[PDB]
Image (cartoon, coloured by chain):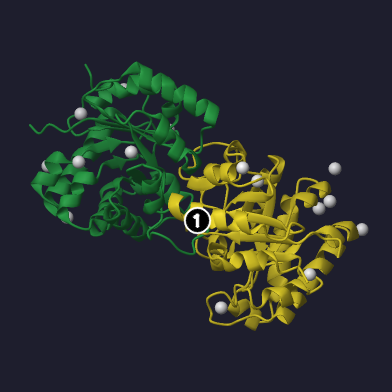
Chain colours: A green, B yellow
């Protein structure tokens, strides 16, 4: 086999306050979840510095987005340099909400991946297909196009060491469709085969491919057991006490 | 004029703990014109720290926000989060958000609605591009953008918490420099629009600020224009000359 460290990210999205953040982080920290699992929280920009100062170094802190240059005339945007200046080392890039609500292109995501890695951050690039794409038989076509753009952005092959991929079944998020652990495993296996052919066997065997569909305390252990599922990028559940149980998904 | 002069400095995507400390110490120590309202619009990651550092004499603004309090909008910041950082202002509809990030008139109106509902004060930005100005569409474009902002105002009293910024996008990064006369012409047209579409009371009280190229050399001549009630400054906001621009309405 290959032994990839399990990775659980909690994407708070546009949620949090000084008061609610303190309560969530105390619960997570006091619970001491599975020591063998890497744990990340992706928090709103306005709380990045305070969350990183409060939270023990065991836990990673990510920004939920960044732009593709260090500074300039981009009112409202945040750079990797500003994320590092807040003491944080991670960023989520190409999240389905950024792609499909805010219209971020594959090429823009590739340029953000390039700039973040150049500045020394670690990145969680997100991929995934919509319902119309899946129904038209374009799951691999869409995912491979998105992966091509991320690969083009990797400055040097060694930098894959700082990448965690998240697959989002957008076709299942906010449609009546539900993705099964079997459907998750099928896509993750296809992504790993893509990495083997287009990057290297060494990168394919070491890279964490995490699942960004609906993850609950009730389904997390069955997903974790799948051989090509190396963890999660959790949405709504990341704000809830069940995030601790999801962090323990790979424990036994 | 009985409209209080208003000078905003938009840092855009610029700042660090170190550079911010130097800029804010210089601004604070300079004690610029106490009769002028001064705002700094800073990157989200520094909002809380800038508001804690700066005396209440200064306003601190976010550079953007979204149109609901919470939800599944990875990367977005709400008015509730801006208030939670101790800040009371937000810039909305900046030319960069409209023309680089594709924010629609309708979205800007919804953001204005949500920010005002949550108790923030707002700086909605309007302005026409070069192709629009050359086609004689300056007023058509500005009035379309103002219609969408007005649709977002929850109740007429809420204009008390609005400062409009006119950005001559046609002049920003086309190499062209807009004259104080060209600024005054647009500001007068916007004030007449407010008189007809809102009220004479709002038209006479609302600050219409200029967001074109403002320098130490042109700021006093712009300030003296009867319908120019201050500035939304870009690059100069990071420089010592921002203090001179804050003093534009003196003498
Ligand atoms: Cl970190
Ligand atoms: Cl490669
Ligand atoms: Cl404030
Ligand atoms: Cl009104
Ligand atoms: Cl009237
Ligand atoms: Na790695
Ligand atoms: Na669903
Ligand atoms: Na493989
Ligand atoms: Na299941
Ligand atoms: Na697994
Ligand atoms: Na303060
Ligand atoms: Na009223
Ligand atoms: Na009023
Ligand atoms: Na210019
Ligand atoms: Na004036």
Q: Chain of mark 1?
A: B
Q: Is residue B48 above or below residue A155?
A: above
Q: Is residue B107 above or below residue A16?
A: below
Residue A91 appears in which quarter of the rendering?
Answer: top left
The image quadrant where one finds ligand 5 is: bottom right
Residue for badge 1: B22
Near-viewer residue (B7 or A37): B7
Residue A21 x, y percent position in the rendering: 48, 28
**In this view of the protein, can residue A178 be seen by the observer?**
yes
Residue B148 appears in which quarter of the rendering?
Answer: bottom right
* Badge 1 residue CB within 8 Å of ligand 11: no
Residue in the image at 84% along x and 68% along y: B192
Q: In the displayed structure, does residue A67 sit left or right of residue A39?
A: right
Residue B218 x, y percent position in the rendering: 67, 77
Residue A60 appears in which quarter of the rendering?
Answer: top left
Q: Is residue B233 above or below residue A11?
A: below
Residue in the image at 51% along x and 45% along y: B76
């Amino acid at each position: 086999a290959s032994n990839r460290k399990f990775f659980v990210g909690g994407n708070w999205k546009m949620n949090g306050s000084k008061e609610s953040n303190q309560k969530l982080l105390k619960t997570l920290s006091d619970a001491k979840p599975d020591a063998n699992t890497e744990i990340l929280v992706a928090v709103p920009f306005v709380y990045l510095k305070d969350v990183r100062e409060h939270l023990d170094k065991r836990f990673h802190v990510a920004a939920q987005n960044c732009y593709k240059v260090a500074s300039g005339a981009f009112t409202g945007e945040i750079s990797p340099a500003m994320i590092r200046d807040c003491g944080c080392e991670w960023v989520i890039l190409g999240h389905s909400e950024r792609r499909h609500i805010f219209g971020e292109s594959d090429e823009l995501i590739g340029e953000k991946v390039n700039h973040a890695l150049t500045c020394g951050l670690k990145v969680v690039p997100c991929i995934g297909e919509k319902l119309d794409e899946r129904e038209a038989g374009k799951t691999e076509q869409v995912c491979f196009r998105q992966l091509d753009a991320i690969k083009k952005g990797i400055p040097k092959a060694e930098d894959w060491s700082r990448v965690v991929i998240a697959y989002e079944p957008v076709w299942a998020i906010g449609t009546g469709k539900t993705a099964s652990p079997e459907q998750a495993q099928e896509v993750h296996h296809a992504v790993r085969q893509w990495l083997e052919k287009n990057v290297s066997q060494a990168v394919a065997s070491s890279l964490r491919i995490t699942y960004g569909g609906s993850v609950t305390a009730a389904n997390c252990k069955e997903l974790a057991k799948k051989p090509d599922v190396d963890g999660f990028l959790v949405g709504g559940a990341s704000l809830k006490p069940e995030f601790v149980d999801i962090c323990n998904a790979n424990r036994g």
